[PDB]
Image: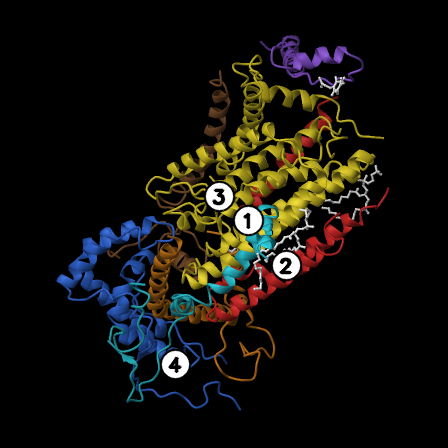
Amino acid sequence: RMMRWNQERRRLLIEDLEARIALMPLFQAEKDRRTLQILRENLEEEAIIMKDVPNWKVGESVFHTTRWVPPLIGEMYGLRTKEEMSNANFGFTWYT
Amino acid sequence: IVELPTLEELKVEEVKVSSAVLKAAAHHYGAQCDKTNKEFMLCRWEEKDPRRCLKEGKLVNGCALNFFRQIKSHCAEPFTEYWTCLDYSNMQLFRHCRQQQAKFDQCVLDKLGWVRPDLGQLSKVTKVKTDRPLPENPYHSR
Amino acid sequence: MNLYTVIFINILLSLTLILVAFWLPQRLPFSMKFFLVAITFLLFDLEIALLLPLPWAIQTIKTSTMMIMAFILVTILSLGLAYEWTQKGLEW
Amino acid sequence: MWFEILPGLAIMGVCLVIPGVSTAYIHKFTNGGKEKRVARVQYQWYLMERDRRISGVNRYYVSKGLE
Amino acid sequence: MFFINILTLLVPILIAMAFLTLVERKILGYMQLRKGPNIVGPYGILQPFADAMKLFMKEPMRPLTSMSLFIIAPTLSLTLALSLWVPLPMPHPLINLNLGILFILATSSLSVYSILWSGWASNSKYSLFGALRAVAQTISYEVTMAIILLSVLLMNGSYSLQTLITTQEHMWLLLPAWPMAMMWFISTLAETNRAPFDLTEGESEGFNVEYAAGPFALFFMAEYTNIILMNALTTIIFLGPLYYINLPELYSTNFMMEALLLSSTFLWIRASYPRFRYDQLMHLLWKNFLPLTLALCMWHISLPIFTAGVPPYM
Amino acid sequence: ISAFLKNAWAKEPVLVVSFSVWGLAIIMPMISPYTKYASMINKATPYNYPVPVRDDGNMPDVPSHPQDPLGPSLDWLKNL
Amino acid sequence: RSRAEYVVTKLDDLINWARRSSLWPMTFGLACCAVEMMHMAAPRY
Ligand SMILES: COC1=C(OC)C(=O)C(CC=C(C)C)=C(C)C1=O
């Protein structure tokens, strides 16, 4: 019975993973836009805040290469409301 | 600079439906629109950046959007019953709801003509040909 | 957090009780076997720690290597036990 | 006879079902009439938070085809 | 709300914890041809509250001893035992932890210290001798206790206690794996220092020797809560109560019934058996049970693979 | 040798069973009609998104709808 | 009532009830009168 039950359970599992797989294209998309937007929002504010700073390039890749590099959590939510940052940082370890 | 795209460039209609809604229609979505879903994805993997493939991303939600409009036009309440029961469960498990699933699945085959994809046949790798060709310097390395 | 909330209530409930308790009523180490047991215990503990990942490793694509590895670990420790049972070990 | 050990047990049992019924209704009342979703893997959280970001400020609120 | 859900899940257990001593002093009684305590209150219902008040009022004599490894020890014992009820998955749990059984195994392991700390703190010979032996069988039994769980998990797929409700939707894990249930039950009897395996603090008065009044009570409370918790873990891991997603309480109703019966069983075991010798006890675990457990552990890594039954993660 | 096993089954009736299991677990995997499935059933379970390849041409890869008859199948998993 | 004296008496009583309901004895068991106590512990009494 255990052999048959887990084989069934496995069939249900493959289905659910297949399900996310299908929806992954979308989420990838929404995130991409959200993420890019997030940066722009904080970056836009950066222009306002670090405005009078001398020799202050509004922003510049800490690196030399010019290729897109995924933004670290801090960068995205750093200048944002504290909580927002906390949520992301300690928001999974702490269950729903 | 950072050449971060502008908001107007990244503003497009949103699906915004409860994740549960999606999981219930997930299988069919994976069926309907899979070609544009994969093209956005194929552009997404090669060119590491999201700067390049956002045009494709707007298309992906655009398909999804009419996918939903068609189900609202026909077989909306069979779907409505299926999602509500699916949402109640904590892990939104598919097997707790099979009676609702059957009526939702049978209708849309009857009216939309779509089909629930058999176990598998969504995981299998797809071939989608896209105009833009892979860039020889993806990492843009010296 | 959710857990923290519960735990601090848990300590509070116990500290409350001990306090009430106090406030309301106003060398031979012969058994190196003991030590021996205890040495074994960690060798077994450590072994458990190696076996603890087996639930995730079951799903490993290899499978053959998984079992080949796991069976070797269990067998070699058990032999360790066996030798504990050959000399005057585990016989306190 | 042995009839009497039951009183005590009754008060044990009643005190071991409360917890299971309690935890399982303070969830269905602090999660909008629906079991509290279980975020075990990153994806379950995403959809959980995506949903939050979807409408209102709470996940149980579930926007449907009519949105 | 969450706070209310902390009262429930605690008080209710504490009140039930009190009613276990009563159902122990009556079930042992009738088995021995005696009514047991019925004169205080109606049918002895007020009896548990009565000695609690007597215990707290009597002087907590601090021996002419440490004063912390003495007060930390009962606080730790009650704290860990009541804490381990946090993740238990009655219907749905209070704090669902993805690695739940490792939490229960780790929290249990920490209680061995309280015994070690209390024994060192007392500074009298009876206490130290008792603690050293007590610590020895507790951790000795932990080694088979842990391996027995690892066999279970591998057939459950995960460490989360919540998964077993979905694993045991068709059959109890006793049918399969009964050989370990027995070995889980005997190990549950050792880890709660109950009778067959209760050499410490025997008629030989170990770590209560110097403990009276409030400290006595806290461990005391701890032991009995544990007595329940471990029995409850048997009633989730091996005896899987029927679960219906539509009505969650029949799960808790049957959890109530099975837990009480297996809690009744260790009460029944105590009156029925003489206590084992210190070495007799370790002879069982290292000679009789550990070879059985390690081998049956391998059988539970093999049963999945060649029966193509590898359990679904998640 | 029979005695080595008849008294060891009467007295010491734990190590006998213990070893027996050790072995039976060391054999069943080798000989079984399902052992192979484990590495497949777990292999199949799709956890990470399956990235699609460019269609240079002349390929048997399922193009378009994954439902295309081409590609891998788990009917072995079904009706298993 | 609230005049403390009454309140005190009631409280004392509770305290007395707890000690008087649960008395835990210890039997040095010198000599034989111990056998007559084991009888108390036993089922008739
Ligand atoms: C006759 O010798 C005695 C004992 O051993 C036989 C006891 O255990 C005890 C202890 C028994 C009770 C009633 C607690 C007593 C009284 C005693 O004197």
Labels 3, 2: front one = 2
Labels 4, 2: front one = 2
- Identify the chain of the residue marked 4, using the numbered disc in the image: B
Work out whether residue D58 or residue E11 is closer to the camera in this orientation and state it.
Answer: E11
Colour that chain F carries in the picture: cyan
**Residue E307, label in figure:** none
| Mark 4 and mark 1 on one chain | no
- Identify the chain of the residue marked 2, using the numbered disc in the image: C
Element at label 2: helix
CA distance separating discs 4 and 3: 46 Å
Which chain is drawn using purple?
G
D60 left or right, relative to B103: right
Which chain is drawn using brown?
D
Q: Which residue is mark 2?
A: C78
Labels 1, 3: front one = 3
Which chain is drawn using red?
C
Labels 4, 1: front one = 1
Q: Which residue is mark 4?
A: B52
Image position of B58 with respect to E56: above or below: below
Colour that chain A carries in the picture: orange
Which chain is drawn using yellow?
E
CA distance separating discs 4 and 1: 41 Å
Q: Which residue is mark 3?
A: E94
Mark 3 Cα shell of 10 Å, populated few (<14), some (14-19), many (≥20): many
Element at label 4: loop
